[PDB]
Image: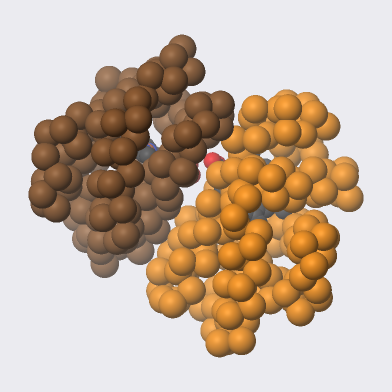
Chain colours: A brown, B orange
Amino acid sequence: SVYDAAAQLTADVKKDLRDSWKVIGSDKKGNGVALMTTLFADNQETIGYFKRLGDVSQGMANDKLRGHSITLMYALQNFIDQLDNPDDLVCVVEKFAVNHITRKISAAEFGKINGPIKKVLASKNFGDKYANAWAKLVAVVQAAL
Amino acid sequence: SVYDAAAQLTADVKKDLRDSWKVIGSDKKGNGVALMTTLFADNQETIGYFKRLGDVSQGMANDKLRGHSITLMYALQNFIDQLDNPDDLVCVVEKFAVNHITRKISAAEFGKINGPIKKVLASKNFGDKYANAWAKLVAVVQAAL
Ligand code: HEM
Ligand code: HEM
């Protein structure tokens, strides 16, 4: 269950999630857009899912993409703040899961976000240990998909 | 015009928004649910729109409502953080506006949130002064509906 995946997050993992988010989460617009653009560059097959955002090749200049990217970072902000209370993390995760379930996004496709996250983390010098930590949080969402 | 509405957020308005948010935003789950139940309590005709959340009269015991309430508080957190930049405030406002436009929520019905906001603010000892400041921010979203 989602609760099982959440309840597994250990103190060391939560520590790595928090320390890396302190940095990346401090520039939500910059790092959020970078995440989305990286996803489109490495997984061109997903572009079709974001037709509402218009021309995503426009990057920062695209207001719809910018608004979406900033908002996405707050979803992660939400997750990070709920880490110490699995019950709350679970209810917020299931809420966002519905958003993607309605767009027919499978657990497998959602995991495509791990590659981009790893690259963004790297640009700030956060290594594999940190990428692995974020992979675990993403798995919580996957458990709901 | 969402842009003209955003221009209404003068230095004094932004200050009152930040000051009051420091207190209310500190307990997103509590004040978030308080906001929603007050809305359902004072405006029973809006309850129909929240069909997916199930039985809202259960309040805090309703996971879906709790997950929704917390997320809503993060939307407000988003707005507050974008106050310095009207271009970014506008693109995030329009993003959330789309979420409600699709739900057939008009500018007038969205305005019904002003009542609950004034009440939640009052219970924390923040008067009309702060309630009006928040009506200004809500007005920005209304301009995009
Ligand atoms: C860390 C990972 C991710 C987070 C936290 C996240 C967060 C979000 C948020 C907050 C929204 C807005 C939901 C709404 O208001 O309707 C959204 C929309 C969406 N997401 Fe994700 N997402 C992530 C990964 C992905 C991935 C990997 C895909 C695709 C394989 C995906 C596909 C979509 C689609 C299609 C939309 C709708 C866009 C639109 O039409 O506005 N998401 N996401
Ligand atoms: C302070 C003002 C408000 C804010 C910041 C706000 C924020 C939000 C957020 C973040 C969502 C989730 C978006 C999604 O995942 O699709 C949402 C959904 C929704 N909102 Fe609002 N909202 C506000 C006021 C209202 C009011 C006054 C109404 C009704 C008259 C309304 C009706 C809805 C409905 C029907 C949904 C869909 C709930 C669901 O099925 O999950 N909102 N709102």
Task: Give percent across and percent down for residue B89.
Answer: 46, 69
Residue at the image position 64 percent from the left and 29 percent from the top: B64
Task: Give percent across and percent down for residue B113.
Answer: 75, 58
Residue at the image position 29 percent from the left and 61 percent from the top: A27
Q: Nearer the viewer, residue A116 or A126?
A: A126
Q: Nearer the viewer, residue A105 or A13?
A: A13
Q: Is residue B132 above or below residue A142?
A: below
Q: Quadrant of residue B9?
A: bottom right
Q: Is residue A106 above or below residue B57?
A: above
In the image: residue B65, left or right of residue A52:
right
* Residue A115 seen in the current view: no
Say how many tags the image has: 0
Residue at the image position 69 percent from the left and 45 percent from the top: B30
* Residue B131 seen in the current view: yes
Q: Is residue B3 above or below residue B99?
A: below
Q: Quadrant of the C terminus of chain A?
A: top left
Task: Give percent across and percent down for residue B97.
Answer: 56, 56
